[PDB]
Amino acid sequence: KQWQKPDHKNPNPIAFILSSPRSGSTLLRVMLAGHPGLYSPPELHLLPFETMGDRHQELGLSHLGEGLQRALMDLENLTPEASQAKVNQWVKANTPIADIYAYLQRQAEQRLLIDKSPSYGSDRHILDHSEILFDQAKYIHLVRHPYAVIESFTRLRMDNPYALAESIWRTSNRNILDLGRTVGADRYLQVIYEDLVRDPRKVLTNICDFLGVDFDEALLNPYSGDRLTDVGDPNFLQHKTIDPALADKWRSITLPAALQLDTIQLAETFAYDLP
Ligand SMILES: Nc1ncnc2c1ncn2[C@@H]1O[C@H](COP(=O)(O)O)[C@@H](OP(=O)(O)O)[C@H]1O
Image (cartoon, rainbow, N blue to C red; front, side, top):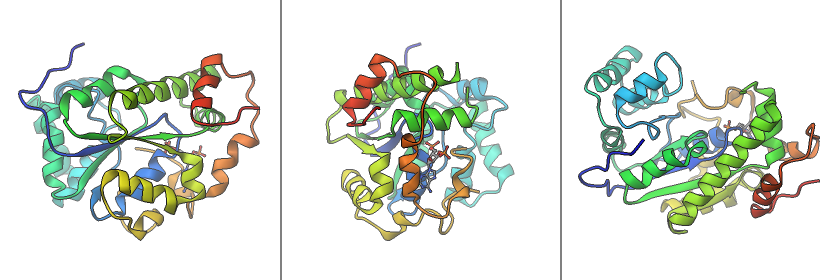
């Protein structure tokens, strides 16, 4: 299904946090929400759709995409009912997704809008929509150890569930890597979850340099103030700090069978060790 090419591409900066699910993407986006020069809301889920009509047809009842309501409430001092009504009106008007991004960029004012998604990378065609819509999109590719993702995906009953979890990690990571190769290092940055949790100050400083903002201490305190956490990780609020022990989860795990040959090659590209 071909993407509608806008009359004029969006020249305004935007950034995405792309990863496989269960990779610390909620932690990273919540860390980023503390920065005063960035706007990092819960999952907008806009990129896979052409218009708000397609989005409504595909999503429907599902709670996925409710982050757009939360964003609007926060950006405009709206109630849930008033937020939903703004969404319902866009739906009725079959409002192009290109317009929703330009709207949020406007409502974010000077702040750099960050669209975090653990599912956009599952389909190369979804990722292709960004290069069609934007001139200056930046991509943060957050990567986690395949064993840690598989174990976590298994536990959460997100679904052989082990083969599907491996497939999703591999598919996403390969698609995001391929996107990164097409755009410059100027518009793509790999972030290793294991490095983020062991030294968040060093990693978040690199992310800030990439996004063109200064480092702010609030980045290190995801559990303080309103960061719009009230989808994403359902267990997120079960932690007190940036937990470095969660990185070493891949060490106490033995999967029912060996990883596939291309899953191994891809994991080696990110310097991971596989026993
Ligand atoms: N405060 C924190 N510190 C370190 N890691 C965290 C964290 N909060 C969540 N995570 C990691 O992020 C994972 C979820 O990633 P995503 O947000 O992309 O779904 C969690 O999976 P588990 O709760 O299964 O361990 C957890 O390992």
